[PDB]
Image (cartoon, rainbow over all chains, first blue to last red; front, top):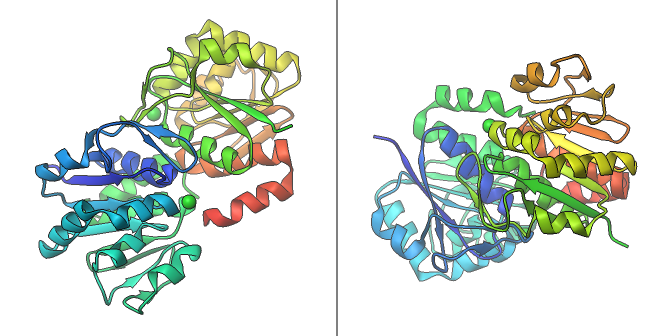
Length: 187
Length: 187
Ligand SMILES: [Cl-]
Ligand SMILES: [Cl-]
């Protein structure tokens, strides 16, 4: 069966960090659900792009499990993810089932908020390092994409394609990732 | 006054090539209007991301002129742009007023359809070269971003940030482009 991804979309999310992974994962044949944190209605992203989610998170969370849970960044979007009890429950279930969790930019700070994956090596946006490192619960990395077991992190808008291809490689293998990569004209 | 950009969004557009330039241009302080070719309703992009436009093209075209007209790619989106009489009129007006026109991936093939900028050096997605070059009306380039006067072209999803920053440089200068670039964590 095809792999399945849950992308959790909150107000103030970074739209490039949302759309690039959705697009790349769909190119890889992954069944992606863009789930709105607040409900079914369109979401106003950080740079005012408005995205219509496929489902509310309330509905999508009942249709798991997912092979990957993806947390976009954007400072305000990640704060919203960090405050959500529903996100907490989803991430703890994914961690308990030994499923992949992928977060980019400010997104990894929701892992801290929900006490996920402590002891991992992680990266974030440079400006999100201090928040992520509060308490010393992770070891910091400057790699553009970082992966420590089932915790896969990345840094910013400009690492989104690399982040997404790393998700594809983890779920569908290096050959599929390479085939998806070539038509993208990445640098 | 702030510069203004018109981004023309058709069904089947490549969503990364739409969202990345909108985001980057807004980071540069440019007033961006995402205008739906078909009307005011949400647009189903090539990889099924659904974007709510700011306005219909029918309305937005009456609120010009714009400092740049931007044509995303995606094979089917570019075909829709190529078939549109409204797009033809907008591009011919922009060319006549010596305004910037920027197109990415399959997007430049709408320049061919509307007889815009013949004699320019252009790039496209590799798979769109033969369509763009039908008749020999342009000279082809493999540069990731190409600019010949007021015709600015680029190649694919993975050149979208570079394309957008080239628009910013053309409108707001190299220093603003460099300042916008740094937080993106580009490679
Ligand atoms: Cl942000
Ligand atoms: Cl396409």
